[PDB]
Length: 106
Length: 106
Length: 106
Length: 106
Ligand code: HEM
Ligand code: HEM
Ligand code: HEM
Ligand code: HEM
Ligand SMILES: [Zn+2]
Ligand SMILES: [Zn+2]
Ligand SMILES: [Zn+2]
Ligand SMILES: [Zn+2]
Ligand SMILES: [Zn+2]
Ligand SMILES: [Zn+2]
Ligand SMILES: [Zn+2]
Ligand SMILES: [Zn+2]
Image (cartoon, rainbow over all chains, first blue to last red; front, side, top):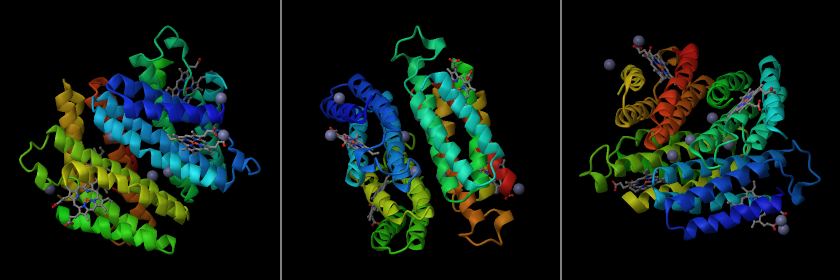
């Protein structure tokens, strides 16, 4: 899927988690976020279209997805353990990862 | 790319790291491995074609890619720091992640 | 060292990173933070003095240290790579880990 | 506790996991391993007694403990999720982390 679609999937599922009642909802939304982050991995953002695929900027861009993927990984373990409140909290915190990338590259 | 193509990319680049001379070679191979791992994320393996996309098996299958992605991440920092030998060691160690998934799912 | 002393070491070094000029300063402060977090690992906080060492709360308390140790780990690689600004950014972000544990257990 | 004691703790509990029947035994042993790894963090090994505390060797020494702590972290989530077999597998795999540090510094 395209970068915009993966970003919409990320945005929509984060909102789902905030509103969620049970573990199943949170688990499913995180799984979907994990897929979208991984699918966005090798995307070239408009701001970096002129840059080398192995430029410091693109390396830093990719690092941001590593960080997001890693945060979703832990949030899902928390949701798998029945720790729904803590998983929702982890989901809120990973917005800073979104924001940090967006500030530089969006 | 298809699962088999991504597995060959993983295989080929791990061999490149083993025989590598300098940091640039190791860095480039690891980046290529990271892209292949990420692109393999949502693949359904032959052995699990009958299974639910959100079965315990498929979640366990995806978990294995989380571990590989995470390992490649650290190895790349080591190579970025000029710690070539330790990056090569890290690449050798992550073979156990390849092996563990293969045993269960290949 | 005691929990309070490890907490002051964490606080003091985080402020050092914010005001830091070069990589060496950031590297040193993060190393000191890493040692303090690790030394804090087996501490029992006043709020959990009556709880079992293997209670859900103590397990969750320790989990917070795992997250902090992990975050410090990645920030140090960034500082090791000369990526000072992104290391400082990473240090800012991990304040959420401090805050999340404090909210529950301080 | 001293380095030798922490290494004995790591060794004894790894053996406990191998022989374990249920989740609770695996969970408790991993938690004990996590405590020992964290307590070993700032130890100076006999082989590096003459080295600077911030030499490449001591940074590499400490990095090995980050790796072990991270591996125990994941294994405990697996045991927490009732995935005992997988947790036991994960505990076997982290022996390579023990071995890799020993080869260099023991
Ligand atoms: C869960 C956290 C995230 C959320 C909620 C999120 C959400 C969004 C949204 C709603 C957009 C606008 C889509 C559009 O352009 O129509 C966007 C764009 C973008 N995001 Fe994210 N995102 C997240 C994570 C990230 C990360 C980690 C990165 C960097 C690695 C990133 C990089 C970008 C870039 C470069 C764009 C601009 C794409 C364009 O202009 O077409 N995002 N994001
Ligand atoms: C860096 C580590 C890895 C390496 C070096 C590697 C290498 C390979 C190779 C050479 C193949 C044979 C495909 C071919 O004929 O071209 C393969 C297949 C396969 N691997 Fe991996 N792999 C790794 C990681 C993983 C992981 C982490 C998983 C599971 C999460 C996985 C699951 C599979 C599956 C299901 C196949 C069968 C593909 C098919 O024949 O349709 N692999 N891998
Ligand atoms: C870099 C991250 C952190 C910073 C900068 C920080 C800072 C502080 C500070 C300044 C104090 C005041 C207590 C004193 O020293 O007199 C404190 C107390 C405390 N912190 Fe942290 N903290 C951090 C992370 C954490 C984490 C991760 C946990 C738990 C996992 C935690 C648990 C506590 C508890 C329980 C107290 C109360 C201890 C007492 O009252 O004796 N903190 N922290
Ligand atoms: C689960 C993994 C590990 C196990 C089972 C383990 C076990 C042991 C044991 C049984 C010893 C002998 C204790 C003695 O000196 O009488 C030892 C020594 C030692 N280990 Fe490990 N260890 C592990 C992880 C590590 C790691 C990751 C490092 C490096 C960061 C490390 C560094 C050392 C060093 C430097 C010694 C020599 C200490 C001395 O001679 O006083 N160990 N280990
Ligand atoms: Zn747009
Ligand atoms: Zn669209
Ligand atoms: Zn965790
Ligand atoms: Zn590392
Ligand atoms: Zn990183
Ligand atoms: Zn000895
Ligand atoms: Zn002793
Ligand atoms: Zn995991």
